[PDB]
Length: 52
Length: 49
Length: 310
Image 1: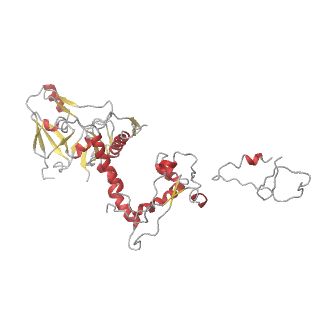
Image 2 (image 1 turned 135 degrees about the vertical axis):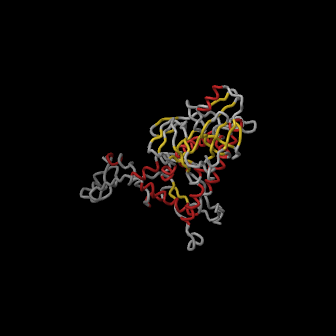
Image 3 (image 1 turned 90 degrees about the vertical axis):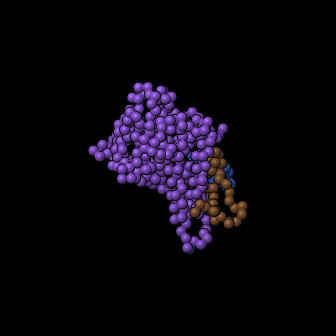
């Protein structure tokens, strides 16, 4: 397994409501000047019993 | 004034805006007396009177 | 397939009002659901009365599961005593060709696979009635296979709105504007459709998928540069607005990453569940079109040559 209680939920439904959440344009992304301004999300999957 | 620069600095970061006064970034000041008066002063301490 | 093929016979009851006899002769090429591959059946077995479920009249979305439990067959020739039809799952004829009349609003092109849909659209709802035998006949509409996958996707997404106390009615194909008639959907078969979704939804997520999720910032940067990448997002996808907020990054390092290929394993599991799901909701596209005297367009209301699709 991964470390317990690591995984967060999705703020995608949450952050889409507030306009005051910081966004990125197509010229912003892949720059580290805005990679820290956006939300950081790290999924883990090493404990998944998946269909295979 | 600084009002041309003050209305401008609220623009976005993802569209660049570079203003260099005398090759230096603008620094702002409220007022100037006879005592300070900084006539041959270098890098851009600007005033807003 | 046999050397002669296999031809079922649907016998007609003797009590016939003569206008209903001429109504059957207009059913020259239609699609008929058989419950079995028994050689001799009745019109009561074919018709909508036996085609109901126990005590409950099925809706349009619930009628799809009733189709895949049965056997689609095509009427060849109407005789005065019986109706001769050929099944589709069984090898169809001695020759390999059947005529199919289009009871469809949309014309057909060569090579396109045909799936079949219940009577759904407005205006063209046409059901043949045999009033001497008090029977009703609801015949399915043959359509091209990407269209049938749209209509199932429009109906299933409509039922998910009903579990949540606009709009989704309008389709487009060949520039034609057309909507569809539906009022209610039973809560039973929607759960059978939805459980068939989410099990196949989950089974695509493997360890390589999170590595693919790190390429979401790459596509939204690449859609700036090429209009072909702009042909993906369409402003209605989640991933355009998902890339504007979430900056994901990769997990590291994977367990036993030397021996295995995580990106390869995520794709093959994706191809067997999510890319399979166009078959899992509706029935299979058993039939495509091969005109012999080459007609690029088979017009609405005409027959067409018919050859199986693997």
